[PDB]
Length: 46
Length: 252
Length: 113
Ligand SMILES: [Ca+2]
Image 1 (cartoon, rainbow over the protein chains, first blue to last red):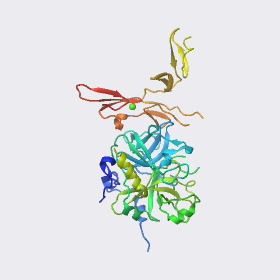
Image 2 (tube, rainbow over the protein chains, first blue to last red):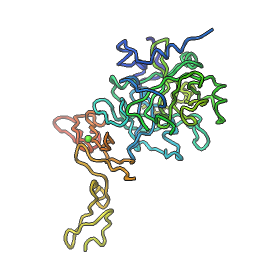
Image 3 (tube, rainbow over the protein chains, first blue to last red):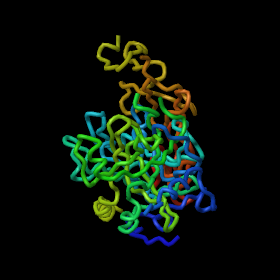
C-alpha cells in the first residue's frame, strides 16, 4: 500500500503514513461485511 | 443513519462522536485525521438557530466508540479541544456552503484497534473516486428516520450522484463545495444520513492502495431518506487547501 | 437570624446566632470557590443523572452520561491525555504527580509541571 504523505508531522501530528488501514481489517487481511459492495461499484460499463 | 445497519467493531476507527457536556448529549459526528486533528461540519459548532454556538470547553471529543450511550471504558478515549477552526467563508446566516471545521486536540491521542486516522484524498484519488455510481460509506449515531436512535454506530453504503441530477433534486442552491449521494428510487435500495450524523465522514476505499479516504462530511438534506431526494456532503478535497493553511499555522 | 444577610442560592442553615451555612438540594453541594452557590455533586464512582422530569440530563464535572441515565466517573488515568505523570483517578477528578521523585509535585484536576 504505497501512500504519499502530504502533511508535515510537526504540525499535523503523527499518523498520516499509516492512515486508512484499519487494525482490525486491512492490517489482519480481513474484510468487513459490505466492503466488497464498494469495490464492485467501481465497475465502469462501456 | 436511515436504513443502514450496525457497524462492525473497529469498522470505522476514525469515527468521532462530538458530545455536548451540558446537557450531556450527542451533538454530531466527526473524524480523526491524525493524532491531534479532528474534522467535522461547521454548522455542528456554529449555527445558533439550531442551538449551536460552542466554545472549546462546551464539548468532549469521544474516539473509538461503538455504543451510542454506554461509556465504553477501556476502549473509547475522551480528548479535550484546544481550539476550534471554522472555515472563514462559512456563513450560517446565509447557507451551508463551506460547511467545514477543524478541531485541534490538546494532547495527541493514542491509536489502537479502535482508534485510527482516516486518509485525506490527493488530486488523483479525488478525481478518480468521486464519480457517479461509485459508492462511499457513511457512519453516525444519528436518528434512524426523519420522524428513535440506534444503540450502536450505524453504517450505510451510498452511491455518488451525478451533479446535474443533484442540482435538480432540490430548489436549494448547490455549490462546488458539496456533492450528493443516495440511491434513486428505481434502484431498489435505500439509505441516507439524518439528524445527528452531521460532521461524520463519507469514506471510500481506494482500489489503488487499499486505504480508506474521507471524500466528504455529512452536511445536509431535506428530510431523510426521501424518494427523489439526496443527502449532501462537504467536498473534502476542494477544501484541502484551507485544511492545510489551518494545520500549518496552528499545527503547533 | 444569621441568614438575613446571607445570599444562599438554595437554602440557608442557621448554625447559631453569628454563623450559618448555605446548603443545597439532594444531589447538589456548595461550590468550593463560591460557597453560596450550588452544583451537582458526587464522590461516588456513579451517581444518578439530573435529568428533566418532563429527559435532557446533566452530570457534574468529571462525570459522563452513561447507560441507565447515570453519571459515571471519568477515569482520566486510563483515558490518558489528562496527566503526563503518575495519575491516580478520583471521583469527579484526578490526582497527577510528577517531577523528580525527590521533590515530587502534585496537582488535582490539572496536568502536572
Ligand atoms: Ca475521575
